[PDB]
Image: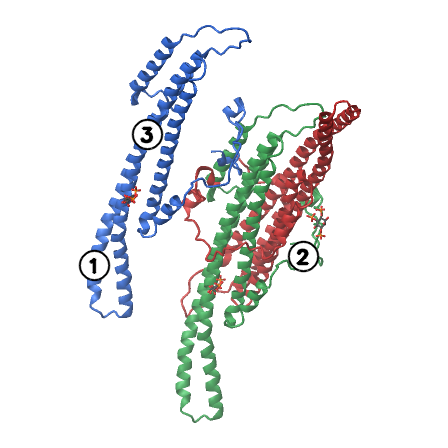
Chain colours: A green, B red, C blue
């Protein structure tokens, strides 16, 4: 980010900013959360009311991840809805405009399925991250008791060293210590392995979806060129338009290329 | 989509589905709109209450586009918020886990700025699409009057052909016809040109953002490999971890590569 | 269909639409089901009230197929009835008009027999499709019991593993499993074979009937040319008409050609 060498949140100029000026900001910027309900805050605050202390930190993230998933679902649904209106608007216009509108409308409506698949994979990653919390919360109580029965024996030794409970308390401490050692080792093992596996799974899906979206956008941009936007003075008639044999071929080729693409066919080559 | 050769919304198997089984669906699917308020429906329904008939179809799309923008903003904000919790969770863990968590946390927090830039460019595209509606709504009333003063002269000719208003009404019809012809030609010219320009502008931003996101995801996946997830039995100590000189270099290289990338350096090559 | 590349149900222009403008829509379009009775819905809803779950899906289609057959029968009956009125109307007119009306009336009345034969063949295809449902509904109960006596043994093993019923329950499971395996294999075999045979039988009849109808229509169109429609001013007498020797020959030739046609004499050659 730009904060890593500046005291202000303003963004330093980049290659894109040098080539083209930064886009103007939004006309309206309301100073509101935009959630529209108390459900988000209630769910965020109710997680730690009764849960164990050790697993609270990770358990808090699951709720906000679910909120992210819901917001992405709403975004995808609304973007899918917009394509229908864009398509129907083209009925009362020229034939070329109507045809281009319909084809680009299905092309842009394609996005919703990719968004839904990405949402499902995000849900699986969230499920694994949730699965970590179960082992953490199971580990905590075994550690608590061993610590408590240590203060117990310390206090009882302070009160009087002639009590016969010293040896049994010490042996209970030894057994609890062995169990806690085993639990503590496996906890680190499991958290490392699960974090690595889940996070690799989550990182593959996003790049796959991004590459598919980029391919769809490129195909749409290639298709848009066929409009033949030329100025005409009043009193003239533009020639009849015939581009169905090109538009249909473009749509079929785009669908086939999107379907054929596989994981090993990734065009992006990071440096 | 899969609807183009099937009667059911189910998706036909693809290369990705053949390689890996489809992800399991979400655990909960509530049968609700999810908007959380009547504002969306109210804004959608109030657009056509008083506006001209010709521009209503295009004016209806602006509101849903604004809703899409707001939902995307909420998604970006929540995803940005999640990274902070992910980062703070790593404090109470092993040193390697904490370091990897912090670095990948900033790497995944990077996404919000790209989302905001895409939102701004989307807003500019929406502004141009709005600008089309002004010319449409200005064109409509000029066309309405010429049609009305035609039924007027027709009715007055039917009533009695000896009235002296025939010639003045006919000439007013001629003048209104000339003005309507000019307006009708320019309307088509302007709508074609503006649609092409705005839609090219909108299609470039999405592919740029997708390529940047894919690069960030690839760099993060490359960074994640350094975890060295190996199983350890209880009673052993893992060697001290030293990977700061690699993690910091990876972060710096990723930031430099993201900054250096330009429009002409697009790796994606559509067929 | 036209939905396979468009978001709207509107039909894209075709060769026929390019050659001739699309026909105007019907004058009246009532927003009603048109069934005229609750019998259709009652029969559709009563099929699954008590039947087995596996065969319900296929059993639901038989009722709607019977409804299709009844509607086709009503259509054929009404079309047959219309020819009688068309023929009787020609009595009070010119001799040539009366003769042409009678001959084309029998030619168009011919259609009803072909429709009845197609209906009978449709009924046979429906009978075979019904015959599939019997085997499906016989297969289901054999599968249900094997599954149930599995949950039974699982629960009884959970309750106490020292019961002596484990071995007898397990052997009953084994025998039911073998029977279910045999039934499951034969079910797939039978459904595939019956579907293929019935659907070939159903597809042959429709093309035969369509070819016969096309031949009849072509012969009628050829016969209609003999009317000699020419304009006449008042005060003149048209020459006496003599075309019985041509009309009777045309009717006889049409009947002979329709009778002689066989399956191997199909003129249609799909690409
Ligand atoms: O049906 P409700 O009223 O919505 O409540 C759900 C229920 O408490 C589940 O046990 C819980 O799963 P977990 O115990 O695994 O957390 C889920 O949270 P989740 O969807 O975030 O998993 C809750 O939404
Ligand atoms: O300030 P408010 O109460 O929110 O009302 C705004 C105001 O009516 C603007 O004129 C209008 O811009 P337009 O006339 O150009 O539509 C805008 O719509 P918009 O944001 O969709 O442009 C509205 O949100
Ligand atoms: O005589 P009704 O009162 O009309 O009732 C008939 C009777 O129940 C038949 O057994 C049944 O054949 P199936 O058992 O084979 O279904 C037929 O359905 P069908 O004509 O669709 O075969 C029914 O119409």
**Ligand 3 within 8 angstroms of badge 3 C-beta:** no
- The label on residue C116 is 3
Q: Residues within 10 Å of mark 2 (few under 14, many from 20)?
A: few
In which quadrant is the N terminus of chain A drawn? bottom right
Question: Mark 3 and mark 1, same subunit?
Answer: yes
**Residue at image coords 45%, 79%:** A146
- Could you tell which of marks 3 and 1 lies nearer the N-terminus? 3
Say if A241 sits above or below B24 in the image. Answer: above
Circle 3 residues within 10 Å: few <14, some 14–19, many ≥20: some
Return the residue at label 2. A3
Residue A197 place in picture, x, y as percent? 46, 56
Q: Which mark is residue C172?
A: 1
Q: Does residue C113 appear left or right of residue B90 in this picture?
A: left
Q: Nearer the viewer, residue A3 or A208?
A: A208
Q: Is residue A82 above or below residue C77?
A: below
At x 22% / y 61%, what residue is drawn?
C170
Callout 1: chain: C
Between label 3 and label 1, give the one nearer the viewer.
3
Residue A202 image position (x, y, % from top left): 50, 53
Where's ligand 3: which quadrant?
top left
Compared to B2, does C236 lie above or below? above
C239 displayed left or right of B115? left
The CA distance from mark 3 to mark 1 is 54 Å
């Amino acid at each position: 980010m730009h904060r890593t060498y500046s005291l202000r949140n303003s963004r330093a100029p980049t290659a894109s900013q040098l080539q083209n000026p930064p886009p103007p900001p939004s006309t309206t910027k309301g100073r509101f959360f935009g959630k529209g309900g108390l459900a988000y805050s209630f769910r965020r605050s109710a997680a730690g009311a009764f849960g164990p202390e050790l697993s609270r930190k990770l358990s808090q993230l699951v709720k906000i991840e679910k909120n992210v998933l819901r917001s992405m679902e709403l975004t995808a649904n609304e973007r899918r809805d917009a394509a229908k209106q864009l398509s129907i608007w083209g009925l009362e216009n020229d034939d070329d405009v109507s045809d281009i509108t319909d084809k680009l409308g299905v092309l842009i409506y394609e996005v919703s399925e990719l968004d839904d698949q990405f949402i499902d994979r995000y849900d699986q990653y969230r499920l694994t991250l949730k699965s970590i919390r179960d082992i953490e919360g199971s580990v905590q109580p075994s550690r608590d008791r061993k610590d408590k029965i240590t203060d117990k024996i310390a206090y009882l030794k302070y009160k009087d060293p002639q009590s016969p409970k010293i040896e049994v308390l010490e042996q209970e401490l030894v057994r609890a210590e062995a169990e806690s050692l085993v639990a503590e080792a496996q906890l680190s093992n499991i958290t490392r392995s699960k974090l690595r596996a889940a996070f690799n799974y989550q990182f593959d899906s996003i790049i796959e979806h991004s590459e598919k979206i980029a391919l769809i956008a490129g195909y749409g941009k290639a298709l848009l060129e066929l409009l033949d936007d030329s100025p005409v003075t009043p009193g003239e008639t533009r020639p009849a338009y015939d581009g169905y044999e090109a538009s249909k071929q473009i749509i079929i080729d785009a669908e086939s290329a999107l379907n054929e693409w596989t994981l090993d066919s990734a065009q992006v080559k990071p440096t």
